[PDB]
């Protein structure tokens, strides 16, 4: 099982890509802060001012304005950005899950959908709706 | 199995309830409009302009607290409860098989997205593309 979620965001692909990798932008829809810009081969410190929690993630692969890859909890993750008429389609993929745990699947799906909804609102309106944690 | 989703919305419970039952407000986050105010015992014709496209029978309504109706073979309840900063909305779509995981995941996505659209609409007065869900 791979949890794949797609969300349309009405802004250019570069702008959506930047929303994730730019330490100053991520706070509007996801982590409260990042240690530095997301680069292929850099280990980033992702803060959650909310739960006063911190986690370190190493960026595995990065294709400018097109792909960000990494892993969490041993689950491969990729955030892709494709062009669409009105702007961009973001596709999040969190791989390797079993059916035995429908509860886990639903919870992760919820996290991805919520984060992408917060993303859409932040980029389309410049306002925020309580960033999520997901991971 | 039931698909339960909860969302915090920072406005009073009465404002969240009116957003669903008032024909003039629902288009900010879900269906484009309703034939009339959602009331217990009425059949409501819902519009979704994007698809230029349904009817639901409102079974129960507890003002500012609960709305229940059935879609297909899945009873649904939308509940509103007070929270310190506003309201906690709980949507429940019932009686799914644990077979079609894709169906459960697709419906979950639907509820989470609708509640997110609701949150922005009520907290910020702006909207993001409404989805049909049903």
Image (cartoon, coloured by chain):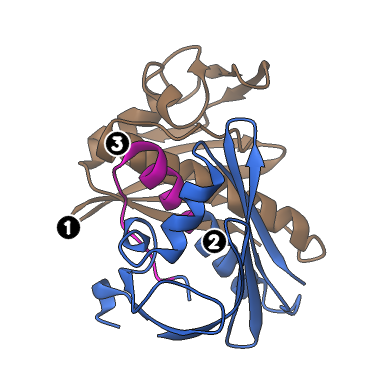
Chain colours: A brown, B blue
Residue range (magenta): B113-132
Q: Secondary structure at mark 1?
A: loop
Q: Secondary structure at mark 2?
A: helix
Question: Seen in the image, is A92 located left or right of residue B98?
Answer: left
Q: At x 49% / y 84%, what residue is drawn?
A: B42
* Chain name for mark 2: B
Q: Does B122 lie within the magenta span?
A: yes
Q: Secondary structure at mark 3?
A: helix
Q: Work out which residue is located at the far top of the displayed protein and give it.
A: A35
Image quarter (top left, top right, bottom left or bottom right) of the N terminus of chain A: bottom right
* Chain name for mark 3: A
Residue B34 percent coordinates (x, y): 35, 74
Circle 3 sits on which residue?
A123
Circle 1 sits on which residue?
A85
| Label pair 3/1, CB-CB below 8 angstroms | no
Q: Crowding near pointer 3: few (<14 within 10 Å), some, many (20+)?
A: many
Circle 2 sits on which residue?
B111
Residue A94 percent coordinates (x, y): 59, 49
Q: Main secondary structure of the magenta part?
A: helix
Q: At x 51% / y 20%, what residue is drawn?
A: A32
Question: Seen in the image, is A58 located left or right of residue A39?
Answer: right
Q: Nearer the viewer, residue A97 or B43?
A: B43
Number of residue marks: 3
């Amino acid at each position: 099982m791979d949890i794949i979620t797609k969300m349309q965001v009405d802004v250019p692909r570069e702008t959506v890509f930047e929303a994730f990798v730019d330490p100053e932008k991520i706070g509007g829809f996801w982590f409260s802060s990042s240690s530095e810009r997301w680069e292929q081969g850099k280990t980033i410190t992702l803060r959650y001012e909310e739960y006063d929690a911190e986690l370190n993630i190493n960026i595995e692969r990065v294709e400018d304005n097109q792909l960000i890859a990494f892993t969490w909890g041993a689950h491969p993750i990729t955030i892709q950005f494709e062009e669409s008429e009105a702007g961009t389609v973001v596709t999040t993929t969190e791989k390797d899950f079993d059916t035995q745990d429908v509860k886990q699947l639903l919870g992760q799906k919820e996290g991805w959908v919520y984060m992408l909804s917060c993303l859409k609102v932040y980029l389309e309106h410049g306002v925020t709706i309580r960033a999520a944690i997901l991971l």
